[PDB]
Amino acid sequence: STGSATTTPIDSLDDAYITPVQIGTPAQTLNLDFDTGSSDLWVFSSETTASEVDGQTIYTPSKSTTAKLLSGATWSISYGDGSSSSGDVYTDTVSVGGLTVTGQAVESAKKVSSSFTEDSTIDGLLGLAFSTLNTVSPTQQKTFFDNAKASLDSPVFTADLGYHAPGTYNFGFIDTTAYTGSITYTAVSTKQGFWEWTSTGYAVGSGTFKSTSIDGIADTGTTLLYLPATVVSAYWAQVSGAKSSSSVGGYVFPCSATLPSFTFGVGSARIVIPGDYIDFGPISTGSSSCFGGIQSSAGIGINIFGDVALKAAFVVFNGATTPTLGFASK
Image (tube, rainbow, N blue to C red):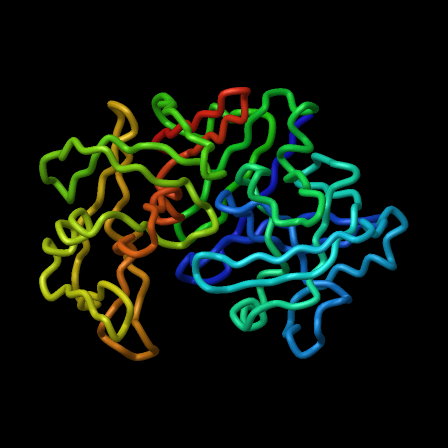
């Protein structure tokens, strides 16, 4: 089997991407944030504290003839950005782009933090990291991909995120028309539960490539590119007037600037992030100070190849017995 679904930016800045997901019988379609940095499929629901729902579409398990309460199971998650959610668990039928899993754990939120409430466009998350990170207790549950894997034509999924445009998540096949040149594959460590790999270096604009190992995670659920302070300083030094602002929470730059590109290495291959991808717009409405899309990972504890990086590539998440990651230009 295979599946193919379009993923759409939630706003004009590509702050996140949503993908429609069918849950239950009859189908209830929710728009979920596909997150290769976590491993829980959780949804706003009829059980979510009413004051914490503000415009989201909810899953109502009592209206699904295939929903079953997973007795005694609870979940609770906290994300790198400080947000969180928790609740109980159902199993139900879940379909993505024509690919169906029966008995998928659907984690129903009883509580969500303010950032989730405040984002009306995201109805929940669909985790695509390794199932070892799943938070369901006392019996850990499998991700949608893990459940689908054995049925897929090939044990892979691909992320093809657009810049200010829709893109695609495919399951079970590689669309050879969706990228240019070849896909370069690179080793993955699953030791921390992430799609963790080592980039071979970077360049700023038309500058020379610096060969240096950068360990980090391919994370579709993180907006920006978070790299070591040395790398980030080298980037922003090429933008007149750019500075790190403690008050704002990172590097800012004059909105009148033209940003240089940023290149990262995948083995001997190179992925070029155009400068415009690194512009996240005014820090507040009407400001001429703009927020940068490349930020320091110092004090995160891990480098994160988020959407800024991934949307410059066609990315293969290869879930073979020994997982790997593939990157192609597009």
